[PDB]
Image (cartoon, rainbow over all chains, first blue to last red):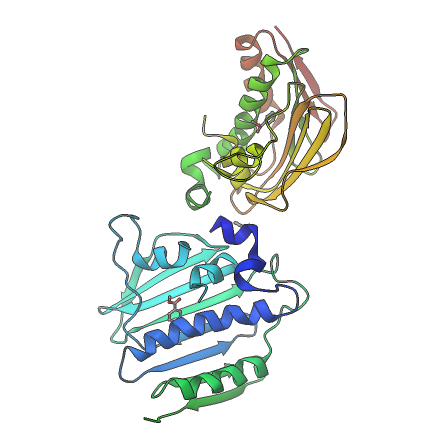
Length: 188
Length: 185
Ligand SMILES: COC(=O)c1ccc(O)cc1
Ligand SMILES: COC(=O)c1ccc(O)cc1
Ligand SMILES: Nc1nc2ccccc2[nH]1
């Protein structure tokens, strides 16, 4: 990840005017849509939290959690730490990132800070559901000037995305003011 | 450097009891001793600053500044960012690190933050002197409980080194309370 840390602008885009900041969300959303399309129900929920973090969750199969034979860490960690631009870029430029994977009846949890895992991916409990949740806090060391998520930029993009992804429910939530939208196109 | 960031204790030593914190200084000092050996005068200065950073200076030749043909960046940056455990470990676990190299009539400067160079090694002026200086601010995200440098832990180790490295002068300075020592065999 040091290559991304060395020149963030080359990977995420302009880190001053807010375009790079919102690209962080849309990179995560693209991965969530890929996960949602693999299942039948297919819903993602994008939430803008009051601390200016954004969480994206889906009810798909869940990111692979088993240990990678070569890398010697969870497949999830390999995806988060090895270089669309990839979620590893988002992780690298996030001062905090929370990963929660529900898979094979188990809840898996891991925390990153500036791309560095704070502990190995851990099974913390049980669940009947499946899916992946990524919540990230953009690094204020990288993202300057424009540091807050604009609802309209996300809402417009997710609406456009819904028509290209049939059967995928996309919910948008703003916990700062309680604003909510639901984009679900069932065509084809 | 991510391997070091992932498990800091395994590279530097215990990050809670002050062991790892002081090893950061000793790793930099080992490099300074190598430089202050092939030079003439042969002196190192270790300074504890009021803002809880430590700087190590030598009056050697200056570490190589030219571009590493394989890596495509300055030889100095390769030493600071690629894996005694090496100064790259100290860089990775320092919230800031300042590098100043005086070599071939030129002063060179570079700043790192958590092991990440903020710009390429750059020529900032002219000088007749030679040597290298590294000042580092240990990361308070890594180093907990014992965060401040104890003078006597440094003084003890630098004394041991002065006997082993008989040709080298070692000065220790504390800018917090004005305390100082000069170890020379
Ligand atoms: C690579 O997968 C992800 O990073 C991801 C993030 C959020 C999701 O909801 C699903 C996948
Ligand atoms: C190898 O380069 C160094 O890291 C270094 C640090 C302090 C010195 O005084 C000399 C070299
Ligand atoms: N604050 C901060 N910034 C960082 C950048 C890279 C790795 C760790 C870091 N901690």
